[PDB]
Every structure is written in C-alpha cells, then in structure tokens.
Length: 246
Ligand SMILES: Nc1ncnc2c1ncn2[C@@H]1O[C@H](COP(=O)(O)O)[C@@H](OP(=O)(O)O)[C@H]1O
Ligand SMILES: CC(C)NC[C@@H]1CCc2cc(CO)c([N+](=O)[O-])cc2N1
Ligand SMILES: [Ca+2]
Ligand SMILES: [Ca+2]
Ligand SMILES: [Ca+2]
Image 1 (tube, helix red, strand yellow):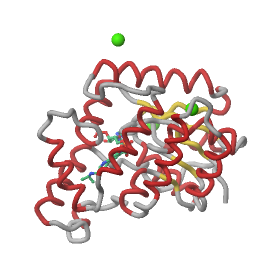
Image 2 (cartoon, rainbow, N blue to C red):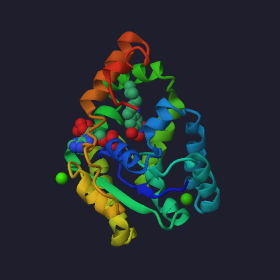
Image 3 (spheres, protein in one colour):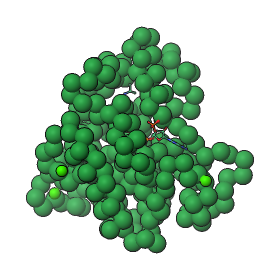
C-alpha cells in the first residue's frame, strides 16, 4: 500500500474527521497526530530527526523521503502535524497522490489551536494540558517535536509563539502557499463543514451510502479529556467517555 492522499491542512482544521473519512473510503489506515500520541509514541524521535534535517541550509531530501516512507508504511493517507508540514516532499514521493487542504476561519482556528495544541506560555490551562499529557506518557520530547514541526510548516527559524498576529499571518500565508505550489487539479480545498460531496468527487468514489461525515475532535471534547485524565489518572478507564476517539 502507498500514499494516495496527502493532507496539507494545519492542526485544528478538521484533520481528525478527515482521517476518519479517508479510513472509511479506503478501509486502510490514515496517519494523524493521534497515531503518535495514542499508538506509536516511538515515532516522536523519528519525526524529530526528519525535522532536524529540515533545519539545515541544504536539507538532504532523500534522507527525509526515507524516513517518511518508514513512518508511513502501511498507511494510505496522511493528515495533521507533523506530516502536513512535509506535503511538498510527500508530493514528490507520491506523484499520483492527491492533496487535501482543510481550512477554516482563521480566528476560530487560532482559539482552537490555543485551547488544544499551543496555549500561550502564561495561560494556566497550559499546566492542565501538561498534567493530562503526563498521564499519557507524553513528555518534553513531544512538545519540542510538535513545535518544531509547526515552525517548519511556517518556514520560520524562530517565532514568538505567544504572538497571535504571527500565528494568524502564518496560517494565512501557509494556506496561500499550498494553493500557489500545488496544481489546482491535484488540490481540493475542503472547508470545515463541507462533508462528503466534494471529497468523494475529488477522489473518484461514491458517497458512502448511509455513513455520516465524521465530526470529531472538538476543543470541548479535548478539554473534557484533559480534565478526566487528570482526575482519573488513566486513559483506559476514561476512554469510554470519548466514543470514537482513536
Ligand atoms: N464535520 C465537522 N464539521 C464542523 N466542524 C468540525 C467537523 N469535524 C471537525 N470539526 C472541528 O475541527 C476542529 C478539529 O480539527 P483537528 O482534528 O484538525 O484538530 C475542531 O474545531 P473546534 O476546536 O473549534 O471545536 C472540530 O470541532
Ligand atoms: C490528550 C490531551 C490531554 N493532550 C494531547 C493533545 C491532543 C491533541 C493534540 C493535537 C495536536 C495536533 O493534532 C497536537 N500537536 O500538533 O502537538 C497536540 C495535541 N495535544
Ligand atoms: Ca532545510
Ligand atoms: Ca506583522
Ligand atoms: Ca455539504
């Protein structure tokens, strides 16, 4: 199995629902950050090595392709960070693969990112995220990898991640750049809420007859998951409160 769909959309743009939609369409796994967090934490250090290679002035792209092939063996599609930041390298590796860009209102995106992924350094909620992550075995190596992959997506060496203007500017620029670099015939821009119609047409499949388009991974659910992880101290003992999570 090889990559058929490359998801270029940023975190908090509907990537987990798209992951679930592609798994329905193809009956084969799709990569997502939640594969790392909940299934393959050993992938963190491999992604870090790939991201480190992007920091060099002249990255060895073939070293990156090699690592990507290893990470993505067995998967038919990618979404979310860290893979989205590698969409150009994936397009070269898989020239027949189609590219998705999931997108949403930038201000809704920023809030979602701040509540789930990248709280500001002085937000007390950041401590709750850290505590709940500790329950999952997630440590500082994960945060470094996630942040470095977002900076690679935004093509920045340093950025003050607490600066909302920079994040909004980079979101807009990233989404613009995808449309500048990917030929339109190979790109579907999927707006949050769009559903099956445009995706199935783009992928040359019928709409799945009696299956609703997924609506997964809301910030409310992620906040509740963090709170329950902290209180109950176990994923397995609370997972049933979050049906369809992983
Ligand atoms: N079918 C759908 N329709 C509307 N919003 C959806 C959706 N599927 C996911 N979302 C929203 O997409 C965001 C998650 O994206 P990702 O999976 O990339 O992290 C969440 O936004 P909120 O945080 O505003 O709730 C989620 O509610
Ligand atoms: C489970 C919860 C208590 N903490 C883990 C959360 C899960 C959601 C999440 C999603 C992304 C992008 O999908 C990233 N990310 O890009 O770093 C980090 C996190 N962190
Ligand atoms: Ca480089
Ligand atoms: Ca500016
Ligand atoms: Ca629709």
